[PDB]
Image (tube, each protein chain N blue to C red):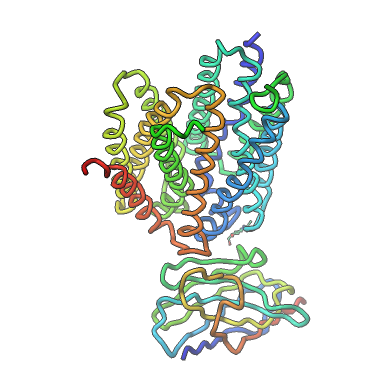
Length: 127
Length: 380
Ligand SMILES: *[C@@H]1O[C@H](CO)[C@@H](O)[C@H](O)[C@H]1NC(C)=O
């Protein structure tokens, strides 16, 4: 069984930066899609960014494009998400998800991912 | 009588095909001003061009002949303007998909440019006028590439200002379009050739070779970015594109000048050039040298024009001028079908979603397989 766990989320002033790390375990992860989704109150679960562990391909949502970068520190089986110039619209709970690499994989559709984290909250306060 | 429409059409074609920003599309899309990833460009954005081109091909052909050509040309100019406006000020992945749709609309409308001269120029003057319009387009593209390279290297211009020049050029071309004479007739609306085995065979190779060529062209720049990241090393996409275009033009000119029986030597030379295209693609894949990847691209582009020129000469040897239009329309439609199947299976996110680091192993294999199957039937 795969087991995703996040960390790094917190209360951050609007305009600052933040880094989120999701450490997968329970298996050898080399052929998985590792993605980030977010959910704020009164809204639906929204794609943030995804990375192909095998090839290193990265995908972003236009909302976070240019500010968020997703990388991989394989030395600890962790996929990191760095968030820069955060705005109030980024307040949400962030869930890292894992999907097996395979034919016809919809990277941005939440239903494609069979493993989900417990969610780490990032609340952005504007002074 | 033929000079006025010919000169106006040639001006429109030149200014439409002069686009300094086209060699540096990938360095622009992946640059700081758009921040588009290579996977997003190759497996989400670029495939949409083939889909829209295939979907819009036949309707655009039917509309063209019926509306007398000119109105479609003007539509092509409008599509050029919209496409570069979106390219200049668009943002996100969806906007780039709209850009690809409009570019596919532009490409599907190119039939009007070449079919226009039929209805306004006498049948005695068709050959020279068509040659003039094709040569003008080729020269326009080569000059645009050379200028793009000159500005980036010596002038130090950015990729944003290369798209401004292309927008100005297409705007001028559109302004030239509003003065072409209205054709007074059309071939089909306003007036079984495949039964021959040779036409079927030559059409097949043309269709398959064209599909492979367009698939390779759509992603060659992404391969160059992969081997030589634009953000950290000097790149020469304008010079390489210009030299490849000139080599292809010289090859096409050479094919016509040299006189040889292509009924006998056609298949052997064709197979040899398909093998050369496969080898060049394999070199592009395996080689870690950016210069070797440029040389392989040059070889592939020059050798393909050696191939498609012979194929087109063999197809049209006996066809009527009226039959040229529908036969070649069917041949480009089938080539688009093949390219769409390829893109769906290989490049699309709903297929293998292969990165560019593996696609060119599939294109080299594709050309080698083409040559292999066509080689058979020799004995037995
Ligand atoms: C792209 O990213 C860079 C660096 O993160 C940033 O300076 C630039 O404004 C972004 N551009 C766009 C249009 O997303």
